[PDB]
Image (cartoon, coloured by chain):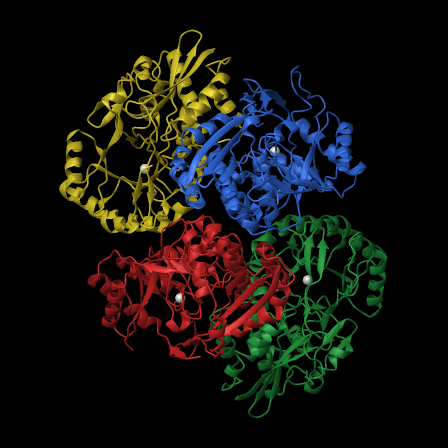
Chain colours: A yellow, B blue, C red, D green
Amino acid sequence: KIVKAEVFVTCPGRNFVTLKITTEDGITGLGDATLNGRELSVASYLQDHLCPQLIGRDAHRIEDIWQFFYKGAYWRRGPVTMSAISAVDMALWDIKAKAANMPLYQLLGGASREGVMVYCHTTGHSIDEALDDYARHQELGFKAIRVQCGIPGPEEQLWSTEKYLDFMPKLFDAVRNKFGFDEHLLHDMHHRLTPIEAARFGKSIEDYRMFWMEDPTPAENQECFRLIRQHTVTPIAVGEVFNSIWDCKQLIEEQLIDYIRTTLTHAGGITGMRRIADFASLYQVRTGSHGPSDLSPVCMAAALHFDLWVPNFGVQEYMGYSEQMLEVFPHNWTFDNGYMHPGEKPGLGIEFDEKLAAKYPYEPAYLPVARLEDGTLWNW
Amino acid sequence: MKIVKAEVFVTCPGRNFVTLKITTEDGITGLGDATLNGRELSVASYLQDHLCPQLIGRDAHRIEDIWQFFYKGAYWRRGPVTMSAISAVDMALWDIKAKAANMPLYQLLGGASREGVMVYCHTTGHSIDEALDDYARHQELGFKAIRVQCGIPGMKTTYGMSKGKGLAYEPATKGQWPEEQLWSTEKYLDFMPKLFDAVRNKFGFDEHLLHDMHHRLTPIEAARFGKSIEDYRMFWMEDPTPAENQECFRLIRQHTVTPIAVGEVFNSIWDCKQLIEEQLIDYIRTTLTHAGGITGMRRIADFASLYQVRTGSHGPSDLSPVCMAAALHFDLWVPNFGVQEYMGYSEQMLEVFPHNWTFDNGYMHPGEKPGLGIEFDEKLAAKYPYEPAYLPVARLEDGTLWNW
Amino acid sequence: KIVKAEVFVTCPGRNFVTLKITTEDGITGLGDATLNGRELSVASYLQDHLCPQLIGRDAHRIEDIWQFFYKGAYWRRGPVTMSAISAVDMALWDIKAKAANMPLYQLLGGASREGVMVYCHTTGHSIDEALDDYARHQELGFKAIRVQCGIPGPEEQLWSTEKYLDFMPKLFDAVRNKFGFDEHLLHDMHHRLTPIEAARFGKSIEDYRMFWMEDPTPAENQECFRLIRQHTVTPIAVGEVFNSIWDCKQLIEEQLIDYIRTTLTHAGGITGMRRIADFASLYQVRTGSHGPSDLSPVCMAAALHFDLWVPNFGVQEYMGYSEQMLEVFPHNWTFDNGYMHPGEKPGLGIEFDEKLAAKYPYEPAYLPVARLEDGTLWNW
Amino acid sequence: MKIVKAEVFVTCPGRNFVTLKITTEDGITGLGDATLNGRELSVASYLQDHLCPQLIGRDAHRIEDIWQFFYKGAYWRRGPVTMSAISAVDMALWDIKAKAANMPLYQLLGGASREGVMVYCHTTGHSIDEALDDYARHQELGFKAIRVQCGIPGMKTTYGMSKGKGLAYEPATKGQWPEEQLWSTEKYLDFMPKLFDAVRNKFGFDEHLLHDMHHRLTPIEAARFGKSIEDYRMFWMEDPTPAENQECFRLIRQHTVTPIAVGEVFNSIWDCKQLIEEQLIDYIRTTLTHAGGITGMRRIADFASLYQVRTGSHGPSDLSPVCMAAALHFDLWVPNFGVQEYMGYSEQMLEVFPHNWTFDNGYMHPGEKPGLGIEFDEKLAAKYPYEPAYLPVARLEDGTLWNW
Ligand SMILES: [Mg+2]
Ligand SMILES: [Mg+2]
Ligand SMILES: [Mg+2]
Ligand SMILES: [Mg+2]
């Protein structure tokens, strides 16, 4: 029996929305509802609408509560809706695993791997800046590195597809010339391109053999990935902004992508993302979960548990966190030579320092938007 | 027209309404509806906490860039909550634009395609006889198109506080937890065609006859049901089966010539693209408040038209009179218009939203007032603070959580 | 209430057919019905058949009049039919915007951009002629330039596909060697090729990264673009000669093109071309409206209004006009550093000098035809 | 044979006809029909102002190059007006070519596939009884195939100057504005199958039974209607739904085995390629005057044949006796021939076009005269100047502008 369903919002120094479920017998569960830029919309969805409906209820019935909130909302999917349902899910699996006196990955089918490969972020204003950044991050032991750097030439940013097409292969060329192959080489395209520009981009970087190119073109219309897929063999990843298998069912069934980047916080929690992962396996599509700063350590934990089990695991993103971010969330995960592992403690193995949290009130922050030279509002 | 104020109001007289009011430097005012039954405060937040402070520097004239700015600029893209917010803005912006133009909004959309807008009512009963009387009542009111339902024998609620035989009008029930209904598809399949039989027998054809299936059946069940009602020439059979998987409408279309409507719960063209392009439906029921306002909904309708799909906008109590006035401008213009749903508003609800549409012999027509032709009495709105109220859920005999 | 629906035909020095609608209260609207080479066919369609039917009628009912002329004609589509209906449409939106005391782009949803990128025409007898032409047009400030030049070796012209395949990539090579990338590089193929020749053409110019190749093969059968699309990543544009969404629905739905070149005068006016534009947006196809001399300034105006609004705007063609052409049409559009903007006056912001117009009677002029060495009549 | 003259004539006895006459250096004459009901002068222009001066140097022998020269050389390619012009040329050119050959035109096409050409008539009534008498009248005239219609009870025009019960023969009404008709699909669906029932009941089978749906229904409506008339074994059900989107015929074909005809309004193989290749129709109703003359129409028919689609050429008052004489040569040859429509011509109309086809017991046969076997009396044509006349439009109860 759930006795309390509480929502917390904190900023050290970025916003996190956290759900805490308490049962009658003292077991306590944590869940991430963080939705970058629309945080208070989810907080209200939970505090005002889902949490009171979680009170009479048996914690054991994870599936039923999921279905109850999924279908019972009537207006069915969506980023806010799912960020909430996933928070409820995450906290209930936290509770169940504690109840099993097990780490979460154990309830899922146990470890399919000894370690979880993560990738880091590297960036510059110039190529030279980028290569020194890659070299220090290689030094830190990551086996997979996502590389970006500036093009020669909400916050509104300026975008030129054309300047990017002509210039950006030059980066991967440099990375490969300095440092060999062996490391996995990654790149985020940030939805900036047309399908046929993405095809062109893919071809032009095939020589450097990317582990993937991610978010090539906006994917509301999943048919738009067909064009890129018929023209390049550079691996494709997508799915940060997805909240549903309905967002990616076509991309996977038509073998248009190699990595699905959906996340526990945003795509349905353990319950939903289990189903998405399993579906992708049939098509030899692998998991490339988003791991930015704006998913809180609660999700990282659960995602290290998920990643430890999934047969078809690909990579985990680990953008990382502030010592200021992490200390609100006492964690027990480890890192060694480019692999992470979840705790071996019951549940998610994660805590929430409420008193510390209360030191940090919500502060408004929005993601940038992109505009052409034109001023036409583009995909950031 | 620099936007100078962007305010959200939550009022409950006596069901919840979320209303956005945008005010311009020169003092033009526009209203937008952002009501999302059962999750209202999330949108209120989505508007109040993130979006309305972003609307403050902006030129109200630039409706498209604003729509795209919020649509894409929210990096997380679709969905009921997000789209409820965006639509409210867009609706308010088009209200302001027609006011600036000194024109009823329909005039800006392309002018009128028709002299008036056909609306349908609902009728119900616990028994077939009851439903026939309700039908006769609405027939004498001049309704040309009527949606009929009635109870499945054996299946009345055992819940003592159910608003029950009401509920078809106001399904969201004041309180904390959703009312739980028991569903049997099998008893529905055997019984419901008898309702349409009896209606057509007593009151022949001449009336357009509508029916809502409330998402309960699977494709092959809906297929059979459509077949079993072909003799009655339904104007439509509505929300047959869950539509997240648009391919699920295929088995239905293969097997019956009963007309198919869907789209109440949709917030985007991406929710219905496949259904339309594949000609799996005849009527698209998406709404201004939930499906992207004037801007987003003109796109859906125009796309639909290419496939000879007509509009059949959802119009329950939980869309505010602002969305209603707006829908009537859209309906009066839209070339591929089919029908408009018109659930009543109580007097209580309407005196908060002074309006100017009219009704005559089954057809509605909006203001000839500039903008939408709708107001929002903030002083009377302030009298009705938010009250929690939630949509039912359905469970099978199993206890299985099912589609409501 | 419309009181007059007048058609004018003038030649300074090229033919234009113009429609002028007057309402009871003095508001006046202008519309382009110019159809190159068949001008008097449209003039008659209007004066003899549509205009008298516009007299009793309410100017506000733009949609209804469109539908009334579209379906009521019984014989439904076609270049002449649509050139007429579009003229009626254009003039009625001119009237409506005046009635709103607004520039037209405002009624459409307002400006999505600060400027409208145009491309110019450049040509030669030789490559050197072409490059000096490009350099002077770059000097004039265009950011997009369509390049043609002669192959070494109605008016009937001679055509050799084979000489063109072997030679024409040599041009883009020269343009890129002299002047860098940055500028958008364009080319018109004039329907001259087979689908598989077009595929070959596309591949061979991929190295120069064209903004587009336009009208690769005749498109009555839209399936003929499939072959080019599976073999090249050079962007494709098409649609000058289209009058309908039915002409291009398959090309867009199957993601066979990147730019749709339909025009207000020829494809249904604001009402029709709004629908075509919107449909193309779903597939990330962008607008590349034809802007030749034989669309009159009335259309240019309205097209600058349309272009200013369309979310999915791509480019506007601006072949340009004679000082002799423009002075019949007092205009208020501007040009600055490769961008155009429509007036800020009510309506289209365009006028028609009738008295001047009457100085210039119609004169017969036809487009060339193309013939192989054979004499077989080919696609010009 | 150098073309020396190329003239357009517009005459009205008493409906409009546009006729092209081509004259050769040696003095062979050929006539072509270019009539486009309701927009006649546009084609007249398209011929007179641009095309006929282009036909002046040319060798009349080169029919194909001429066809392509105008087809492609008009940079703007298809369409009712353009194609009306091109067909008129082509028809005149093939008339000249058979004259040069001293042969009836059919002989040049491949010779006769049949001894004669089946034609269908129309019958109508305000009531079913009336229509049955009209049926009996045409049955005794020897017609083997008959198209039947009649009024939908309640829906007679309230317009005092309507030619009304006529109109099925000459729908284009002299004047300035189109006559406006009110349409109800729902009343059509409930009533019309009763007409076919009554016909088959009084006069059994033995007659081929045809019916024109006039573009009024949507795919699922047409689907239902086809189903509802299966018992009567219609020879065809015609123009079911607008066909700009050829995919719209799919829902129809999936649901009924009632035969489907379409193509009156088509000007090109591109208008019907998908419909044929997908086997969505049984009869292709394109015409010599509107669909590309002998040259373009042999292509359409041959393509159709691959799919077992037969020809069912439209033949109303608004195709001239030149197009009729031409159609009978085409029909007599074409292997996949289905039926020919034969609306009468008044005596007035025919004395302008001295002809030589014959009719015997429901079958027509063209001249055994060289060329088409048709003339054009220019002196009597000159007596009847052009009179404006326009096709109706239909509006729904709504005022909505709909498909006529
Ligand atoms: Mg990304
Ligand atoms: Mg419903
Ligand atoms: Mg071109
Ligand atoms: Mg017909």
Residue furthest to the top in view is A25
Q: How many marks?
A: 0
Query: Where ligand 3 lies, by image quadrant?
Result: bottom left
**Quadrant the C terminus of chain C occupies:** bottom left
Instruction: Residue A140: give x, y in percent of width and height.
Output: 17, 29
Foreground of the two, D321 or B146: B146
Foreground of the two, C223 or A188: A188
Left or right relative to A109: residue D234: right
Instruction: Residue A119: give x, y in percent of width and height.
Output: 25, 32
Residue furthest to the front in view is B26
Instruction: Residue B344: give x, y in percent of width and height.
Output: 66, 32
**Quadrant the N terminus of chain C occupies:** bottom right
Q: Which corner quadrant of the image does residue A340 belong to?
A: top left
Q: Is residue D298 visible?
A: no
Residue furthest to the bottom in view is D26
Q: Which corner quadrant of the image does residue A87 belong to?
A: top left
Left or right relative to A130: residue B85: right
Left or right relative to D138: residue D240: left
Instruction: Residue A283: give x, y in percent of width and height.
Output: 39, 38
Q: Residue at x 74, y 32 (%)?
A: B195
- Please tell me whether residue D281 is drawn above or below residue B39 in the rendered image: below
Foreground of the two, B288 or A191: B288
Q: Is residue D20 visible?
A: yes
